[PDB]
Amino acid sequence: PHFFVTSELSVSKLLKLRQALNSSAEGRYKLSVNDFLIKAIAVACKRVPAVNSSWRDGVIRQFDTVDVSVAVATPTGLITPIVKGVEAKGLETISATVKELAKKARDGKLKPEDYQGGTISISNMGMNPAVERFTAIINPPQAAILAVGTTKKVAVPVENEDGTTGVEWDDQIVVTASFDHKVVDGAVGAEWMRELKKVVENPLELLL
Amino acid sequence: PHFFVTSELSVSKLLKLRQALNSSAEGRYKLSVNDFLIKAIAVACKRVPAVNSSWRDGVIRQFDTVDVSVAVATPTGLITPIVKGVEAKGLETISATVKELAKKARDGKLKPEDYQGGTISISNMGMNPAVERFTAIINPPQAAILAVGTTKKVAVPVENEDGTTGVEWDDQIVVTASFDHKVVDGAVGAEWMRELKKVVENPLELLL
Amino acid sequence: PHFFVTSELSVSKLLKLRQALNSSAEGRYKLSVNDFLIKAIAVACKRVPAVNSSWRDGVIRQFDTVDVSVAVATPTGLITPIVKGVEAKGLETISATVKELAKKARDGKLKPEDYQGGTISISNMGMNPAVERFTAIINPPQAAILAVGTTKKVAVPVENEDGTTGVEWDDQIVVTASFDHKVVDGAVGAEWMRELKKVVENPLELLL
Amino acid sequence: PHFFVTSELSVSKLLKLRQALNSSAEGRYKLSVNDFLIKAIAVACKRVPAVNSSWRDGVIRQFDTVDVSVAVATPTGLITPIVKGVEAKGLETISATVKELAKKARDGKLKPEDYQGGTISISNMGMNPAVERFTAIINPPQAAILAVGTTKKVAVPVENEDGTTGVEWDDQIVVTASFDHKVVDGAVGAEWMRELKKVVENPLELLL
């Protein structure tokens, strides 16, 4: 039994900072927004340990550390590469590890210890238009799986009192979050979502 | 097998009237928007009796009266206090009964006859940001369960021919409605949703 | 196990062309937007054959041709009239066949070979307000079922550099797409959705 | 035999970000500039492992992880509390751990496993005026010890072509760095200093 948590999330600050940091990238790495998202979900899963947990048969094993089983679509299908100790990783570690693992998934294979649904399962379709949102199924060894739709620029009130509400156009992804609903719950799921959104909206705390 | 009915709903009129009525509140009560929503879902469940029904084993028992099993999140978990005969109640009856029952759920306990999923199950996360919408699971003794996301102020065309479409910013909650799909159906579910939205949008008919 | 693909879709071009073509209608037919949508989903199911397939017990039978089991709500319930070889049909064939079949469903009956969930199951609530989106359940003999919410006019950036982003108000339906998830997958489902959206957004390719 | 590496370092960006983050502090923590410096020296000691090393009798043991033996002046004398795995810590972990450890040093005692000169010895007199710089002695179990003078606001060319060089006043600490000179060397010491200065000057990379 799965419940869905749907949460928009602006990115313009994080897009700006990724731009400035991929400028700061010397060709040394490619920072995808997803790398910051991976470190941010690491931050939030440390923040909310219920997400970085797993449905054990009798109990729910909660994982102190967080890794991410990012899911990469592959010609084979869906490979879920596991990026380990993200919260203690770097983020170019996230960068290379994500691109390396997706490479080894589509190009070669990953060894089976790469597909653990580790404490959190992430499927990202931010790059995929026509899905501003979409829903997946939680892994049985998961606690909750997160899916991200595509980025949209939308009308937003602009504080400016000259154009009082005004029309100000924000980039943002509204995401869905499928939850196994017994290992994790709607309140904690939404709160983890808000942790994620907070840390993402300003990379300044994601710096930390 | 559950189907989901997703329905935005403006509130600005009802927010205005709640403000004016909580001004009219002499400290005698606190009218939450949810109290008006409870009376409004009572109105709509009398309007659409399929919602205020229950999946009996062989049949679907349809309930003439409507009560609401509002669901209150509790330190224990989810308590679903039952507010009885809402359609014939007052609304400060709704006010106090909802706050009293949530109190006795989080603070003490409610006696078990308070958790009946009575004819309608309501979970409200209007107060909870980062969930503009979310989906729940229908109670087996329910017919359909309703979930409300948070309120959002959004760009809206303003009729004014000077700013022709213009940008006019409306508060509204888009809600999801999980339906057991055999006791209740998509057409009747959506129509009950529209009944609810109609009665809510203007409290003038909710007065009645 | 079903996954949901949610996709907005503007219509203003197709609304314009339907208007011009129902002007071009001499009373000879009534072209509902849904007729163009039926030819467009035929186009996309030829484009994406995974959708116009069926869950066989052992395998997934993929259907070269596409028909549509459009679903018509009936006083009996949901009749799913089958419109055959849509991709090779006309569109006034679509027009009359859809209206004729809905007629025979609500008025009389359709003979049972009209309810096959043929290669694609379509439920349309574009005409139904208060459901900008909604989700259904895939037919077992289906591969994926599509549901369309209602049309909404929304704030949209207008390119004009005078009103730089400006506020420009577009009609569009955001649709959900419930997928059986083993006969069909999220990537192919979303891509079929984008095929559909592309062909719909400009009827010029839907002409073909 | 010790050599000294002297390096100014602007702070205004990091002062701004600490201000904004101690505004972001909800009373939850106090972020001293030294906490960011501790995470930054962790970053640089991972960056330059020669600093987070120790003079073993025959060899130099280089430490993969970095901790910091921050030194706190105490009524007893100099307590060198050890903050462990800083590079994998948080920074409010740094915040509380530094203030807690200094507290337990001046107020109570730290248990002896708190004074290890762990991989790096830091003495900070940024808070101490009249020492814009000062030099210390490397711990024998250290590889290099770092000392920071006080912050000074100084005349700086301002790019502005109106006031062409102009006079623009920057806050900065010039630091000394005493090095045991056989476990570590002038080139690597200065380069570690530049790593430190780079990561500090913009907390954006210190975010990571």
Image: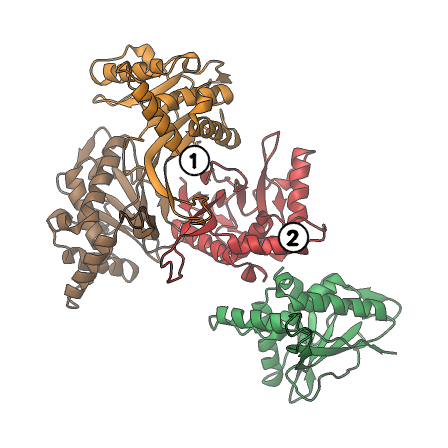
Chain colours: A red, B brown, C orange, D green
Q: How many other residues sit within 10 Å of disc 1, few (<14), some (14-19) or many (≥20)?
A: many
Q: Position of residue C152 (x, y in %)?
A: 33, 38
Q: Position of residue C178 (x, y in %)?
A: 41, 31
Residue type, label 1? Ser
- Please say if A131 is above or below C144: below
Q: Residue at x 71, y 69 (%)?
A: D197
Q: Position of residue B34 (x, y in %)?
A: 24, 53
- Please say if A160 is above or below C81: below
Nearer to us in this view, B42 or B165 = B165
Q: Is residue B153 left or right of residue B91?
A: right
- Please say if B163 is above or below B45: below
Task: Determine whether the residue tagged by mark 1 lies in a helix, strand or loop.
Answer: loop
3D distance between C-alphas at marks 1 and 2: 31 Å
Q: Is residue C6 left or right of residue C23?
A: right
Can residue D39 be seen here? The reply is yes
Nearer to us in this view, A86 or C197 = C197
Q: Quadrant of the C terminus of chain A?
A: bottom right
Q: Which mark is residue A22?
A: 2
**Tag 1 and tag 2 share a subunit:** no
For disc 1, the marked residue is C7
Q: Residue at x 41, y 31 (%)?
A: C177
Q: Quadrant of the N terminus of chain A?
A: top left
Pointer 2 indicates a residue of which chain? A
Nearer to us in this view, D197 or C139 = D197
Q: Position of residue A200 (x, y in %)?
A: 52, 55
Q: How many other residues sit within 10 Å of disc 2, few (<14), some (14-19) or many (≥20)?
A: some
Count of numbered labels shown in the rendering: 2
Q: Is residue D189 left or right of residue B151?
A: right
